[PDB]
Amino acid sequence: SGALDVLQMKEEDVLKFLAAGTHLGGTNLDFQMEQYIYKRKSDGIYIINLKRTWEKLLLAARAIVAIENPADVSVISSRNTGQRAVLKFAAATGATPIAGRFTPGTFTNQIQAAFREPRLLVVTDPRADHQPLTEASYVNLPTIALCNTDSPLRYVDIAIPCNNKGAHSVGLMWWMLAREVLRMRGTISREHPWEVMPDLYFYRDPEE
RNA sequence: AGCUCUUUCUCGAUUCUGUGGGUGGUGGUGCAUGGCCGUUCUUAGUUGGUGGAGCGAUUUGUCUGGUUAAUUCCGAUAACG
């Protein structure tokens, strides 16, 4: 990766990726998502490479580190699956969540009381949260998000591929994201098991 | 009706007369106007701020749907209050 094997993907994490079905990706493709895919099966389903997922995780996370204030890396998700995941993210690591409906004009107003000026964004799924992306390009925000095979790239600077159609793929990926930023900034580093797990970043899932 | 005329007393600077200038008018103009009233209109309509969309006139907000006597609420939502 960069450093020889003290940042490179371990044998452990491979099991978690495959158990959460992150490697699988939808039938439809884009021409900006061609390189991330390796190939197709004998059936409609296209298998994302996990090596290529891993490199994109790192500089994405390293950019979340690079800011000197952790209270203005505003995360956003509006899908139900991505509500519980982001809430733990921005609770654990200093960040600002915007859960549910966006309520437009919150990055360009001077009258609204939910007005904020962050630096980064971390979005789940471009085609549920298209609204904050358009407003990001009016006030110079860097942008990161989780793309799928059929999610187009536009007003995003870096992608973090994932299966993310509402799965354990979602919560696992947000957990891993918060794990990495702590290895560089925090004192959680040792790279041997963290107390917090991905078993509460997964969906609410209506119970009995 | 001393209004006028005949008649011949009375009042005393308040006046009369000329010019300049006022004043009054249910005189005109409601197509010069104020105010008031009627009517469009007894229906549910109306507007600005900041942001968004347009070269602009403008538009969004002030709504597909459900609901109410009612722009009355629920809900939706590039609009928010």
Image: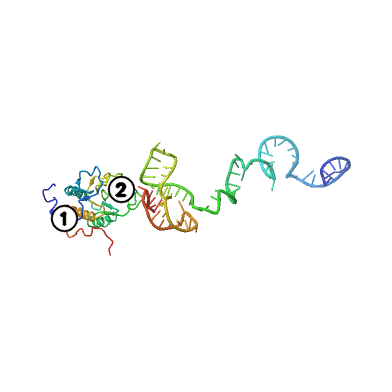
Residue at the farthest bottom position: A208
Q: Which mark is residue A198?
A: none
Which quarter of the picture shows residue A194? bottom left
Q: Chain of mark 2?
A: A
Most foreground residue, A143 or B18 = A143
Residue at the farthest left position: A4
Labels 2 and 1 positioned on one and the same chain: yes
Q: Give the x, y percent position of residue A105.
A: 34, 49
Q: Amino acid at mark 2?
A: His
Q: Amino acid at mark 1?
A: Leu
Q: Give the x, y percent position of residue A74.
A: 27, 51
Tell whether B7 sits left or right of A84: right
Tell whether A208 sits left or right of B28: left
Q: Give the x, y percent position of residue B18.
A: 73, 35
Q: Which mark is residue A15?
A: 1
Label 1: few (<14), some or many (≥20) within 10 Å? few
Of marks 2 and 1, which one's residue comes earlier in the chain? 1
Most foreground residue, B45 or B5 = B45
Indicate the quadrant containing the C terminus of chain A: top left, top right, bottom left or bottom right.
bottom left
Between marks 2 and 1 in the image, the one whose residue lies nearer the viewer: 1
Residue at the farthest front position: A42
Residue with the mark numbered 2? A130
Q: Secondary structure at mark 1?
A: helix
Q: Give the x, y percent position of residue A116.
A: 30, 50
Most foreground residue, A125 or A64 = A125
Q: Chain of mark 1?
A: A
